[PDB]
Image (cartoon, rainbow over all chains, first blue to last red; front, side):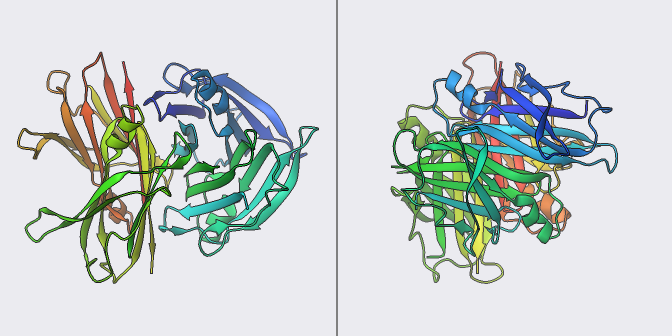
Length: 115
Length: 115
Length: 115
Length: 115
């Protein structure tokens, strides 16, 4: 699988477990088509979203349901969700890890792209 | 003005100047209606996007055009843009400062909300 | 004043108020000499730590007392403090803004350096 | 091993490879005693720094040589090094992952503490 998402909780210093997310691919009509989805594991990671065959070049959006995560912890958050929008490019062999580091009023996201 | 956006460049250690952004508000039909737009100044700030009267309760999206920013500096970055989606004013009028800290393969965004 | 520190609280979405910090300068004998200290204001900023005359070339350390900040809010955080160590003015006088974004188990620090 | 350090490069979107770091433990005389050191692997990780037996409660400092990393890439950085200072606490079974996300003028560090 060429795409993995990892989510961390900066308040508790822990993986962010059971965080739902949806992945979309931009269609020719410039609308977001559902592509894959899941929830993070006990390690904060979501594996197996796609395959090398299906993950062709294009524009993808990962929508991470951060608001429901904070609400389940009784913490009022700022964002509705965290959005990660990027172009997958074929250049050479490539694997994508999208990391998201969550706080109630702040998040960071990083792409680690390796061969 | 109750909404201000500030953008910093973590590669240069500078304000991120001339960064375009578009603000949208979710309409009754669940579509994103264009609300305001502008570009950051020499201080990396964008002021005057809206007024207290116009900035009603709702769900807002700030789309920060980070890819164009990096490309003009010779850098091919990971993200298409940075999106900041949030409910505003649902406990009454507040002032919102949205900060974004940019690197080619990573960004963070923070909200400072004052009454 | 050529050195200012700004601290934000990523749990509350607020300036981090009353955050103590101590600034040191590396002496000729490689020890850290106390240089300046203070606490952030209601805006989360600490101004007036030094003057252009006193802020000579050197290696400086800003020790931000984050643990005391979190403990007063009922939180037991991971870090003892946030340290920011940098060479200043080695290409001539500059203005330095050090920003720190705080969460209980994570923080970021950014420098904005202007001429 | 109860302590692992992982370093990412936010400019290139890659593990930060061959990053040197030194770990210190605070001694009773309040000085920093060398404890362990190493360089990150091709995965940006440094494993095997210590053992459960040796990693007793106390105050530890991880000093990450970020300046040499950026200098090897021809990029002028702001910080002399990144410092992570924390208390190891025995509470229950615990493993510590210290993550550092590096940009030339900014870094973030996060602790992921798991059982």
